[PDB]
Amino acid sequence: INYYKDAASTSSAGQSLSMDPSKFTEPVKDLMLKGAPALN
Amino acid sequence: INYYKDAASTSSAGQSLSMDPSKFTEPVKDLMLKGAPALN
Amino acid sequence: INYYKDAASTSSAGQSLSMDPSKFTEPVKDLMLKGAPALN
Amino acid sequence: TVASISSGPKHTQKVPILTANETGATMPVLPSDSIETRTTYMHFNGSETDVECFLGRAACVHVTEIQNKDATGIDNHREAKLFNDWKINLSSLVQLRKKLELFTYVRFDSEYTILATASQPDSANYSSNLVVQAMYVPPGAPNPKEWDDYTWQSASNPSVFFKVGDTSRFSVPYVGLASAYNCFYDGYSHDDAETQYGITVLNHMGSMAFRIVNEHDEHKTLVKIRVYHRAKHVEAWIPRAPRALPYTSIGRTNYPKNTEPVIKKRKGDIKSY
Amino acid sequence: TVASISSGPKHTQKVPILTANETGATMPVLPSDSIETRTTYMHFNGSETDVECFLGRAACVHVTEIQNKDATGIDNHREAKLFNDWKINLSSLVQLRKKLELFTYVRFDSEYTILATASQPDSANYSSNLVVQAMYVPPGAPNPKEWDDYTWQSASNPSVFFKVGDTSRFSVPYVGLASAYNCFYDGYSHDDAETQYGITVLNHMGSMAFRIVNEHDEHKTLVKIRVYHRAKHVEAWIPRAPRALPYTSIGRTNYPKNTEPVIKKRKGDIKSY
Amino acid sequence: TVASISSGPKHTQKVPILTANETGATMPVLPSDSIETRTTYMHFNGSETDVECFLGR
Amino acid sequence: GYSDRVQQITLGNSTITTQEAANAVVCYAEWPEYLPDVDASDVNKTSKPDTSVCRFYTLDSKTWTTGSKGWCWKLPDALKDMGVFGQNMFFHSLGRSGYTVHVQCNATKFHSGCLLVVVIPEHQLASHEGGNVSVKYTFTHPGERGIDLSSANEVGGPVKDVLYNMNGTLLGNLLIFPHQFINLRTNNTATIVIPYINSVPIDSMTRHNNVSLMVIPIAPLTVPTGATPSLPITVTIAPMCTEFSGIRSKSIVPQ
Amino acid sequence: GLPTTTLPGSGQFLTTDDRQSPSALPNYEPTPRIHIPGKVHNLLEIIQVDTLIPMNNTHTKDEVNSYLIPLNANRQNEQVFGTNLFIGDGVFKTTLLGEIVQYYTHWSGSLRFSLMYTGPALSSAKLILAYTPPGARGPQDRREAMLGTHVVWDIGLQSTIVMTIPWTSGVQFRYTDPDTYTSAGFLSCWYQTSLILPPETTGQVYLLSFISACPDFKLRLMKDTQTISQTVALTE
Amino acid sequence: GLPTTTLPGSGQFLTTDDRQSPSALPNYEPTPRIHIPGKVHNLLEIIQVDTLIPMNNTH
Amino acid sequence: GLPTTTLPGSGQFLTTDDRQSPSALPNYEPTPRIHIPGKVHNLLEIIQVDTLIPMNNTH
Ligand SMILES: Cc1cc(CCCCCCCOc2ccc(C3=NCCO3)cc2)on1
Ligand SMILES: Cc1cc(CCCCCCCOc2ccc(C3=NCCO3)cc2)on1
């Protein structure tokens, strides 16, 4: 129950439960498959 | 009504109403019947 | 609404609205009718 | 509901007003058995005479006192009121007692309110703020000996901490050993030739102990505890004659010697108005 | 539920009362196996002996003390009780300890209540109003060194601020590293020839630190902290023999030398009543 | 959720543990690519590492 | 014609027969079983030597005499040197096991005496020094020799006082632990099956013992007239459902 | 803003109340539970396991010997042991039953008292155990004893005898701390015929005695035990 | 957090008010009731039994 | 007026609690979000990127 009118006044947000490290761990242009050779 | 998000914050648990003394009072391998001889 | 788990914690009881003085006012073994003679 | 029905002249062989009181009954005679009446309604239910209502308001049952002071060199805390215990019991202050003893057996839940106020009878710079800790102490329970014993840990014993000036309130289920509490008991705890007699051998809820949690300031502070008790969920059996003479002891029926006549003497004749 | 069934005379070849205790069992013998009984009902559930109930009330687990005073020229705040830390731990005050050690492994959530009261043992004009700040400080956590270090910023570490005289209350989930807390541990932290032994190497919740946020007034104020702990959501495995001798140390089973006989000697014979 | 799957001996032409870090990637290698593992579950969600939680006290 | 009395336990390449048993106890009514995945944490596949480790090792014999106070062995310690069980033990980082314990003591129908055979999960011993003196490693790792409760206090060792179970509890209440009596007049062996009991799914076998087996004379040995005044007691123990994990170099432990 | 009124008791801390609290560690994930044999749910589960009673209390320092009740060969008519039944005190007090009863104020229910015989197999004996319900004195001779609850025990192949002290009471609860009104009786044991040892055998034989509660049993109103105390906080 | 306002009378103790309270003895089981003749429910029940009047008050 | 009781902990400030508060700036409209590459949701996302270890610590 929100007792207040504005959105800033609500409690903390709830877990992204998004999670996708590939923008950080695999930003390569041509896709690399694990097990296939790195450099062909 | 829980007012809080986490489970630790809820009140005391409610009675097991489990109760089974046999693990402590009769841990024998071959079942003993009351009234039958203890050692055959 | 009870906020508490135990019965002792609830408020006062509510009126018997029982009321039967005959155990105190007429505990006689043979029933006496008003208007009939007391001793026959 | 009618309080009176309409009734007119009578010339009968059926006389409801002649009875034989030797029988032990109180025959239910009404105004309309002996005068001519008109209808009237009751307009009333008898709500406020219910035993739950009669025993259901808080009554002061105990006033004790403890002090906060330097215990340094005190050989007997209990004796310095460094903490004080109360052999729990409900028939010590007398107003509520007469009310309960209108019945022989009584059963109910208790709601306790504890008010604590402080006094500083001799020169203090200020009023300190003390926290009281009253803890239940039932029979066969290690008893506190100093005001800061291991006892006060109260790991298994219910205790409440509140501030002096405030009030504490909690409710205890009916803790009697039998089905009801005996308001009276014409027995002994065993057939001993010298054992005590009456209710004290049966009412044995153990006792309640109070202390201040605070260490001492430079002045001394008197804290006086008042315990109030309210019966809730009341059940009462077997009415008895009300108490006429004054009380002398917790738990015995004894009255004082050379007491005074309790029935008011007429100023005049039997014939006087 | 029947507590006893009705049972009459017996003349059998089937004797339930003869057993062989060497087997390790406790055969479930009842009054009705050896006397003639009548039916009676239990009228009871065993509610208040549930382990959740047994370990579920607040027990005092720790009393510490800190003071508010001018830190000017104090070379060691910790040492002046300008703030004090508590190597957290639940087996130091002993009432709750005996209760927990009835089990080998225990798992539960904790609810802490912290009561703080102030004392002014020497001449003050008044009672000041101090705010306490107890902050959690787990292992491998920069430790406070002065009563007003960067540590107290506590940007990532849960801390509660409450007023002296009041109480603070919060609840911490079961923080054990394993599936249960070991009440006992017959091991070492590694196969070292001189490493310590027992539970202390396993119970390593880190510690809890307290301080007053207020700067100093002209007088000095003693604040004494009492931490209460209540287990909620209890789970206990493997019952053990209750503690008989007194305790000497947090985390070891050791008892004192030349202790006294714990079994009461008869005043009379084996035959005595 | 499985934290580790069961995996046994390997004698392949397909080597997941040889990579080229010059590429800028961190290849997602697991215990089961180089030892024999048994199944185990995570039992955990990563709740308390959410940025809302990290900056939220 | 089956009696509670005669029994055969075959485990691996070894068999035990008793013609005078008194049933058998299975701790907490649970039988040893391997570690399920749902309970697993370490990702390593475990090693289950089976029949080469799950057989019966008979420890060296003790001698019950009228002065005996009782003996105490710790598991897996007592077996630290038995065959391949022991090797596996020193060579893996973690291991887990249940056991069948069979304690033997026969006499004649003229002797009297009664031993308590009990298994105590997590038996943390007390220092006889009091205070917070610890009990050094070696002292709680006696190996097959076990601890002799009638031996003298030593320094860094545990207290050996029997009315207190070596920990501040009374001998009389040891009966809350899985146990069985050997009463010369009834019984000649005691057998207890121990499931693996720990707060972690698998642990180190060298830094932590998870049960102490204790044999304690309670009704003193009384031999017939002009009999030799003593009887030997033998303990045979078999690891069951053993699993080892995290193999490597081979632990080096004090002393 | 909703109008409220606060009642007496506001701000109090009652160690026995059960309410919700904020978690200090928001979002933390506890370690998974694994299975452990032995879970206890009720103290009523464990007080049904029997434990030994130091009946032979007559020593002067605690010894293994106060668990042993001695028996003499060839005595006739005589008394083996006696005790009152204050389960919260005296012999009972250190037993597991005694030890738990002490965490509660009231108890009700039946008790199971058993004796296991340890004499040579070629000996024989007949004993009588008697329970004397409240109201009479501890019996002074078997004649007196045999008129109340009793079992003639014949020592045989079956080594133990289980006597039950059936709940005999006016009031439905008794106090665990000993008190009179609430007292439970006496337990005595006498030779019914007598112990007889085989040839080549000699001396005393002993009985071990246990106590546990029947499934009948009720304990209520928790409190603190007189069995443990302390003078300064312990440290590491 | 829900916004509240406290009214006059907050914190007072009125010996006649009737509200709920926490039980000090959570989970305790009271002794069963047995039957007892004579239960009273209203004081109105008993004032209908007649009793003697010391009319001759002149002593 | 609805009867209430306050519990232990009233008035405390726990830096880790999560509740509602009045907004000081009623009705204010925040700047629109635009898209920015790189959003992080969990610290678990970033500890999977490898970084160099100063293994040769001997300086
Ligand atoms: C006649 C007659 C009838 C009665 C009943 C007396 C029983 C009342 C005593 C029982 C109250 O028990 C308590 C329960 C809890 C606490 C307590 N909890 C926290 C602090 O104190 C104190 C007493 O007494 N005389
Ligand atoms: C046996 C046995 C079992 C146990 C369990 C001990 C664990 C209890 C310590 C953990 C409590 O953790 C805390 C969490 C939060 C805070 C805190 N939050 C704000 C202020 O303090 C303090 C401690 O210990 N011994």
Image (spheres, coloured by chain):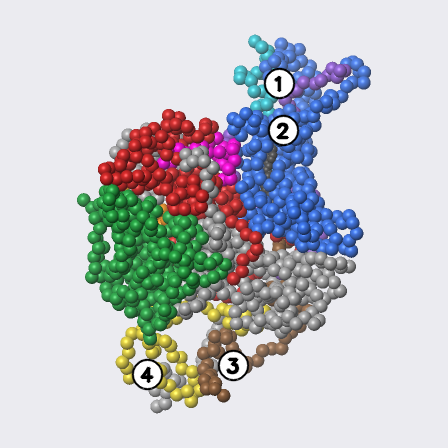
Chain colours: B orange, C cyan, D blue, F yellow, G green, H red, I purple, J brown
> What amino acid type should be assigned to the residue bearing mark 3?
Gly
Between circles 2 and 1, the one closer to the viewer is 2
Q: Nearer the viewer, residue C6 or H229?
A: H229
The reply to the same-chain question for discs 2 and 4 is no
- As helix, strand or loop, the secondary structure at mark 2 comes to loop
Across and down, in percent, residue I26 comes to: 54, 46
> How many other residues sit within 10 Å of disc 3, few (<14), some (14-19) or many (≥20)?
few
Q: Could you say which disc has been placed on residue J38 in the image?
A: 3
Q: CA distance from mark 1 to mark 3?
A: 96 Å
In the picture of the structure, the residue carrying the numbered disc 1 is D27
Q: CA distance from mark 3 to mark 4?
A: 31 Å
Would you say the magenta stretch is mainly helix, strand or loop? loop
Between circles 2 and 4, the one closer to the viewer is 2
In the picture of the structure, the residue carrying the numbered disc 4 is F15
Q: CA distance from mark 1 to mark 4?
A: 109 Å
G14 is higher (above) or lower (below) than G42: above
H35 is higher (above) or lower (below) than G246: above
Q: Nearer the viewer, residue D143 or D54?
A: D143
Q: CA distance from mark 2 to mark 4?
A: 96 Å
The reply to the same-chain question for discs 2 and 3 is no
Q: Is residue H175 magenta?
A: yes
Q: CA distance from mark 2 to mark 3?
A: 86 Å
> How many other residues sit within 10 Å of disc 1, few (<14), some (14-19) or many (≥20)?
many
Q: CA distance from mark 2 to mark 1?
A: 35 Å
Q: Chain of mark 4?
A: F
Q: Nearer the viewer, residue G144 or H223?
A: G144
- As helix, strand or loop, the secondary structure at mark 4 comes to loop
Image quadrant containing the N terminus of chain G: top left
